[PDB]
Image (cartoon, rainbow over all chains, first blue to last red; front, side):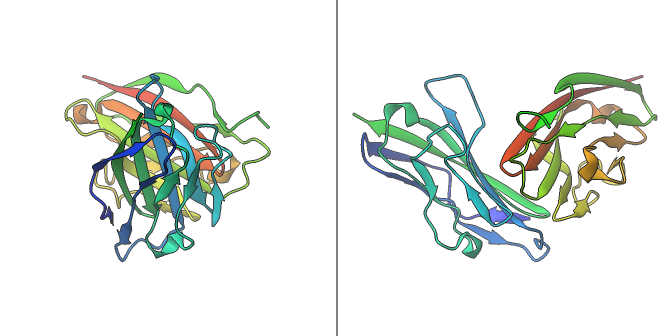
Length: 121
Length: 124
């Protein structure tokens, strides 16, 4: 088991600003496997869902590799292993509106949490 | 090599009778950039409940976690003795009608990710 301590919440920011989407987690004793973190986006302005935007796996970050939000979504912490899977989305666009899901796995534990993002003109 | 991480026949239905063993295939192919650690997860969305995406088995850090997950505990296991060769398949033994649902095979070898869905039908 594994818990994401951030609550599901709605972040509202203005176009062109930076959105911080928190995702902080704690581990249970059996979570001894490799830390794996992913974020997915389900945008409001298209019917595509669960698209990967960022991944931490094998102690490497893959961010711009994923086309959605390329160049604009990055992990905020310099130590993800300390329990901080949060991300920043820079230069917010109206197309960024949607539901973002943080997925944290440290085998065998798994947890997920959704953050809703609204961008204001 | 494939152009991107790929699973053979990514959406299909498997049908078996109650009490039999179902073989749920998930055969994958890597692309040249998939250099991270292999990770494989299967999830169930049962037809008899509102729960979706419940983990039933995981291969991560070269370890298998199966009965650790309560759904189908004791009855779902990987079939291959060499998952790294491309065989992420699982079998479900002594099938029950409550096993009916959508099973998802998720294969990750960073940065590649691929998914497959199997609709499992159990016949009386």
